[PDB]
Length: 105
Image 1 (cartoon, rainbow, N blue to C red):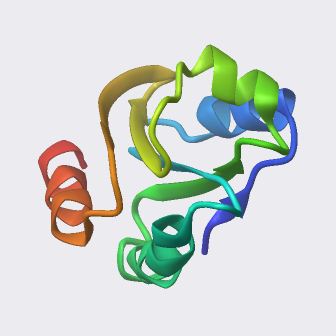
Image 2: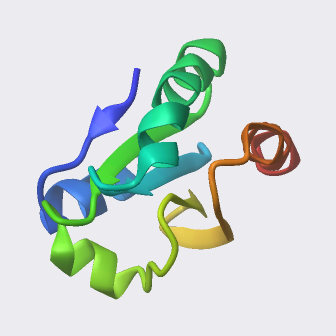
C-alpha cells in the first residue's frame, strides 16, 4: 500500500493529492540494513491505516528530493499534512513510528 516515489514532481503531486490526510514518507537507501528490515512493518502500517498515505523515497533514486527534504540519517520518516511538514525523526523504531502516526492522523 506504499506509493513508490520516482521523481520530485511525483513527490509534490502525492503531497498535493493527499487532501486533509496525513502523509508518511520513508526515506531509505539499499545499503541501510534496518531500512530493509523495517520495510515490511512500513507496508503493514499502510494496510492497517487505509486512512493515511504512505510513500517510499530511495535517496539514491531521488537525490533532489533527499537534498530538499534535508535528510541525514537512514531511515528518516517525515510527516506531512496539506503540503506542510508536521513531524520528523530518524531510525528504524517501529513503536515510535506507529505512535507518531496516531499523534498526527
